[PDB]
C-alpha cells in the first residue's frame, strides 16, 4: 500500500478474470483468487509460443472517478494478435467487461490521486490443452489480472539512452506487428547487453537492412524535427501499433497544432530532429537523451533534460488519462 | 496400444521428469505423474515466450535393447537455446539422465520392433515465477515427458509437397537458430495456409531477400544434385541446426560416398537437383515431391516415389536408430 515507492513489479492482487475456450466458443468467464495458471504439459503456449497479451491502465481522477484509457483499442489490437497466431478472438464487450470486472473487484489497489501510480491490467490469451506437434491449440485461456504500479519517473521526466543492435526482435514479415511473446523473447539478449552497457534498452532498426528505425523494445519511437514543427514516427509492418503512439499522433495534430508524419527515420540522419523519445503504456513517453549507433553517441536535445515538445505531449496525454485535461471523444472509459 | 495406427499426437504416458531452478541452481529433479504444469499467472514463459524445447526418440531394437539417438547433441543444442533466451543451462549429465529416467519408467509405451514406431521425448525449459515486466524469469522449470509416436508427415518414404510463403518464421538476426516457441508461433498462420492448399508445410526462404531456401519450419531441407553425386543443404544463421541434418551430412560422406556441401540453394535453381527432402526427428526424411513457388510447381523426381539417394540415406539413418546397422561412435546410448 506504500504507493510512493511502488515500481513496476508483480504484486498479487485479490481477483483475476479467467475465461476458457473449447469446442468453438468462450465461456462466460469468472473471477478467481488463484493467480496460478494450470495447463497441459504439452500446451502450445509453452512449446510453440502461442500466446499474446495486452497492457492498459486504470487511473483514479481528482474528483474520485476512475478512468480506463482507450480499452477499445486494446480489444482491437489483441484481436489482431490472436488472428496472427490462429487463436480465437474476444469481442470489445467481453474484453472491456473483463477489464472492468478486475478493476472494480480490485479497486482498493488503485493508487489514489496524488501518487503518480496506476492499476496496470494484463489481459492475455494462451493456447492450452493436450498436444505435441506444431499446430494451433484445441483449447485456450483468456485471463486478466492487475497489478498496482507506482510512478514511472520518480523525479519527473528524465531522459535515458538507447543503443542500436545487430539483433532483430522481429522478421520483415514476422509477428512484430502483433503483441506476442516471441517478439519479446528475442529481445531478451540484446536488451540484456544494452543494459550491461548502461543503456536503458536497444533501438531496433529494421530487419531487412538496418537503416531505418523500428522500435525501442517496449515502446514505439517518435522524433520532432529541429524546427519543432513536425512529429515523425516510423511506419513499418513489423513494429507494434502502439496505442500511446497513435494517441500522441492525434494529440500532436489536434492539440499542439503540429505537423504529423508516419514515415521512415534513417539512423544516419538523426540530426534532422531536435528531440526524440519512446512511448508506451508503462513508460508513457520516455525522453531519449541520446542514441548510440556504432562509434558515435548522438544526443538530440539533452542527456538530462526532456525536450520542450516532449513535455507538452507527455503532460497532455498524462492529464487526459488522469482526468485533469479534457479527453478526446471515445477515449477514456469511466469505471 | 495399437502401434500400427500411431501418428504424432499427444497420449498421456505414466511418468514425466520435472526439475526446478531457483536461487542460482537446478535441483536434482524428480518423476511425477501429473502432466499439468502449474505456474504463476505472470510467468515469462506465458507472456514473453521465454521457453525452449528439444525433441528426440528412443527406439526398440530387434535384439530387445533400447536405443536413444544422439541425446548429447540435443543437450548441447538446448544449452544454446537456453543461452539465447537468458535461461539457465542444463548439463548433458542431467539432460540425458532425465530422458533415461523417462524412457525406463515408461518402457511399456515403447513401440515394439516391427512397428515403425518410437518413443518421442519432449524436454523443455520455461521461465516461471511471479513477474510483469519484460525480463528473464526469477525461476525456471525443466521437464521431460514422452509420447509413443509413428509418422509425422505420412509414412514409408511417401513424398509430400511444400509451398513457398511471403511470411517469415524467423528474422535474419533473430532466434531462428534456437529451438524456441516464438519461431513456431510465427509459422502457425503460413503453415495453416499451406495445409489448406493441400501442402504438407511451407518451405521458408531467407528473411532478408527471399531468394534462398531456409527450411520447412518443422524440418531442415536437403537436395541431391542431378548426377546424384552430391548432397546439398542450406547454410544459414537463421535456420535450426538440425541433428538429423548433421547426421545425414555425416552418413552421406562417410557411408554413401557422396560429396557434401552446406551452401546456398536459390529457389530459382531447383532444376539443379534430381531429388529433395525434408529431415528431422519427427520427419525422419520426408521425400519432397515438388515445391510450389508462385505459379510454378517443381517436381525433382517423383510425386509418388522417393529418389534413390533419398532412400539410401533413409535406410542408413533409420537402420542405425533401430539397431539394424552399425552406429557411428558416440551415436546411440543404450537405455
Ligand atoms: C515492442 C513494443 N512496442 C510498443 C509498445 C507500445 O504500445 P502501447 O502504447 O499500446 O502500450 C509496447 C507495449 C511494446 O511491447
Ligand atoms: C524448425 C525445425 N527445423 C528442423 C528441425 C530438425 O531438427 P532435428 O533433426 O534436430 O529434429 C526441427 C525439429 C525444427 O523444429
Ligand atoms: N508489454 C510491455 C508493456 C508496454 C506498455 O507499458 O505499454 C511490458 O510488459 O513491459
Ligand atoms: N519439435 C517439432 C517436431 C520436429 C520433428 O518432427 O522432428 C514439433 O513439435 O512439431
Image (cartoon, coloured by chain):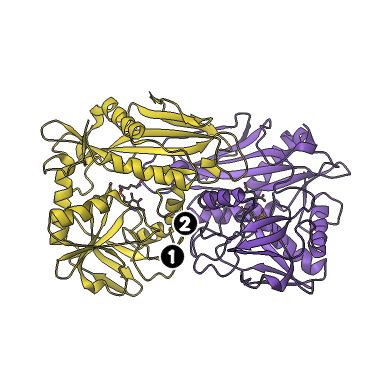
Chain colours: A yellow, B purple
In the picture, the disc for residue A207 is 1
Can residue A155 be seen from the camera position used here?
A: no
- Kindly indicate the quadrant of the structure image that contains residue A53: top left
Give whichever of discs 1 and 2 has the lower sequence position: 2
Residue A162 percent location from the top left of the image: 31, 62
> A231 and B86: which one is in front?
A231
Can residue A315 be seen from the camera position used here?
A: yes
* In the image: residue B248, left or right of residue B182: right
Which quadrant: the C terminus of chain A? Answer: top left
Give the spatial CA distance, label 1 vs label 2: 10 Å
Check disc 2: other Cα within 10 Å, few if <14, some if 14-19, many if 20+. Answer: many
> A144 and A77: which one is in front?
A77
Tell me which chain the residue with mark 1 is part of: A
Q: Residue furthest toward the front?
A: B295
* In the image: residue B28, left or right of residue A75: right
Residue B163 percent location from the top left of the image: 61, 58
Q: State how many labels appear.
A: 2
- Kindly indicate the quadrant of the structure image that contains residue A294: bottom left
Does the residue at mark 1 contact the one at mark 2 (Cβ under 8 Å)? yes
* In the image: residue B266, left or right of residue B249: left
Q: Which residue is mark 2?
A: A174
Asked whether mark 1 and ligand 1 are closer than 8 Å, the reply comes as no
Amino acid at each position: 500500500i506504500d504507493w510512493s515507492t511502488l515500481g513496476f513489479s508483480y504484486i498479487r492482487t485479490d481477483l483475476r478474470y479467467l475465461a476458457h475456450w473449447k469446442d468453438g466458443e468462450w465461456d462466460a468467464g469468472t473471477l478467481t483468487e488463484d493467480n496460478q495458471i494450470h495447463l497441459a504439459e504439452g500446451s502450445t503456449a509453452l512449446h510453440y509460443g502461442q500466446q499474446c497479451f495486452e497492457g492498459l491502465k486504470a487511473y483514479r481522477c481528482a474528483d474520485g472517478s476512475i478512468n480506463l484509457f482507450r480499452p477499445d483499442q486494446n480489444a482491437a489490437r489483441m484481436r489482431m494478435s490472436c488472428r496472427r497466431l490462429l487463436m480465437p478472438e474476444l469481442s470489445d464487450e467481453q474484453f472491456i467487461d473483463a477489464c472492468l470486472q478486475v478493476v472494480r473487484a480490485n479497486e482498493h489497489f488503485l493508487p489514489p490521486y496524488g501518487t503518480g501510480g496506476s492499476l496496470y491490467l494484463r489481459p492475455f490469451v494462451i493456447g492450452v490443452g493436450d498436444n505435441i506437434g506444431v499446430r494451433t491449440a484445441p483449447e485456450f485461456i483468456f485471463s486478466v489480472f492487475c497489478v498496482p504500479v507506482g510512478p514511472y519517473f520518480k523525479g519527473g521526466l528524465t531522459p535515458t539512452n538507447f543503443i542500436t543492435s545487430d539483433y532483430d526482435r522481429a522478421a520483415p514479415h514476422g509477428t512484430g506487428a502483433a503483441k506476442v511473446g516471441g517478439n519479446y523473447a528475442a529481445s531478451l539478449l540484446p536488451g540484456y547487453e544494452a543494459k550491461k552497457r548502461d543503456f536503458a534498452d536497444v533501438i531496433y532498426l529494421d530487419p531487412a537492412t538496418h537503416t531505418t528505425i523500428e522500435e525501442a523494445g517496449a515502446a514505439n519511437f517518435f522524433a520532432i524535427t529541429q524546427d519543432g514543427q513536425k512529429f515523425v514516427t516510423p511506419q513499418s509492418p513489423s513494429i507494434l501499433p502502439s496505442i500511446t503512439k497513435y494517441s500522441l499522433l492525434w494529440l500532436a495534430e489536434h492539440r499542439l497544432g503540429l505537423e504529423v508524419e508516419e514515415g521512415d527515420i534513417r539512423i544516419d540522419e538523426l540530426g534532422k530532429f531536435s528531440e526524440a523519445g519512446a512511448c508506451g503504456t508503462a513508460a508513457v513517453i520516455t525522453p531519449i537523451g541520446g542514441i548510440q549507433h556504432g562509434d558515435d553517441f548522438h544526443v538530440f536535445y539533452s542527456e538530462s533534460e526532456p525536450g520542450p515538445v516532449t513535455r507538452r505531449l507527455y503532460d497532455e496525454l498524462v492529464g487526459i488519462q488522469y482526468g485533469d485535461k479534457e479527453a478526446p471523444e471515445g477515449w477514456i472509459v469511466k469505471v
